[PDB]
Amino acid sequence: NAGSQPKLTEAVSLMEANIEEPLSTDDIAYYVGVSRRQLERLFKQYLGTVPSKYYLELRLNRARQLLQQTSKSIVQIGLACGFSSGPHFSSTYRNHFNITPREERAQRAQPG
Ligand SMILES: [Cl-]
Image 1 (spheres, rainbow, N blue to C red):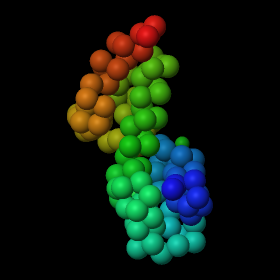
Image 2 (cartoon, protein in one colour):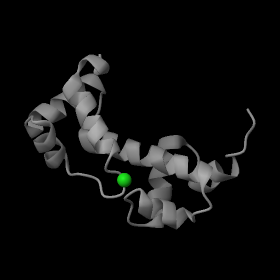
Image 3 (cartoon, protein in one colour):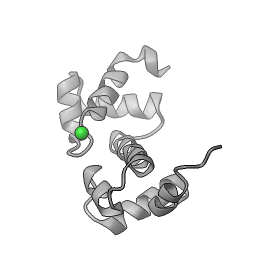
């Protein structure tokens, strides 16, 4: 279970501190003190994915937070979350959340 895997939770905390300019997987591993292979094994075992893909999920969730709370353009938000084009940001966002960034912002005020 992830909370009982301190190395994995450490890596995730480090990733959370580096969203706009994300660390390479190798750099996460160096800073947490495991090999790259070991870091990959942790992510595969305790989260079910690879570190780079979890990092993308994290950056997409920060983007969702910005879509719900700012008037920053779609382009601005994509750049702030490490994306390098609008089409790349919006397409990956839509694949992940099954709505577009524009739809997420339109729906931010949903009162439940
Ligand atoms: Cl950041």
